[PDB]
Image 1: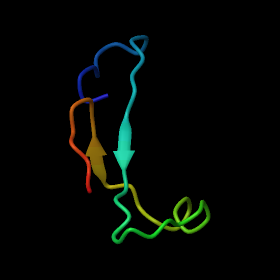
Image 2: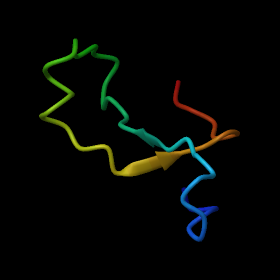
Image 3: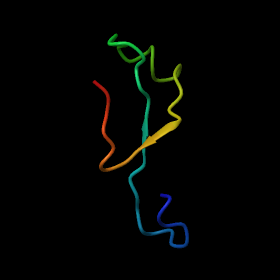
Length: 49
């Protein structure tokens, strides 16, 4: 979305990534509605260990 803002018929794909702190695995309700997706990911971003 940070590419196009002048045309309302271009379509886009926005990826907001939340990095789980440890190697833990929150299931779905410990993340969605509770955690905040502030970091932005895109095509090329290298992810953690």
